[PDB]
Length: 197
Length: 191
Image (cartoon, rainbow over all chains, first blue to last red; front, side, top):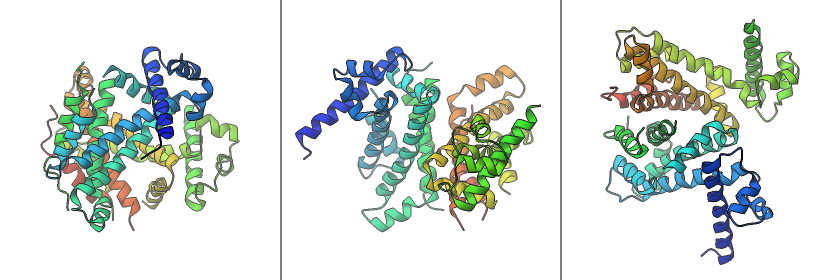
């Protein structure tokens, strides 16, 4: 149970983040000021600055939240599914509504502040994927999970999984409406991966 | 004429690496890098926004040695085989080892490293497209726009990077690991 007072602040925070994304997509980053984001979220600028030091920080949580929900659905997928299945299922269950994703991903390239946020997410996603995968193979055993998450095989598989969605996203953002199918196809390369070696 | 700049810039990067390795990043300011390189701090910030950026050109030299070897591989060879040839030549140290190892500690440096690896992908797509083109610049252009190639280049790049990370982590060239990781592209539809 988190307090109603914290739940309301956290909701306000995410409303600011969404309003930021919604402005950046409509009108770009350059023309958008912290005070327009505040106005769009229906809050005073002081409220804006309670949560975010800059407008780039306001939108930064969306990148993270989408990566972290994907990672989570990879872990929580039903146990019997194979890793490609868990991965691909999690993609479908978490990363699908597009044009709002497009410009955001394109901002991760053109803005220096968001280039760093995007790098941080990608790395962070790669690491959580290592952890989720180790949890799917560990059979409840912490010592096994630790050994697996140390493994270059899992680090590599996670980079590949990460790269599967990232390349689909980036290349799509820089023709075909579904970056999805491309991401899903990409992930299929992990079918039959050798987890030991 | 620009050769002198690229030279100053390589010298700054080598100075940085020497200090980072020998005393760590925290003890090293952009200005100590300057002095070690014999340049003024204004000169330093003309090339590098931050001290961690000053090590990019060292990572870049290794990465582009690999992209180059892919380009220069016998033109008969298959892309997968070209990648194997490039890995073989490239990977077949301790400055590299520790520089990469330092990134484990520092997010700012890890960012610079990750960034260099990611630029490499663009070089790879271009290299791979040129081979497959068999000639036509416009074949090569069209091929370079294809997702399948973009994904293959990311996977090859990861194959080497994660190998290199694990190697740098280790006491044993990363060749072993990279090839093993590359085997994931066996049977890929290059198209």
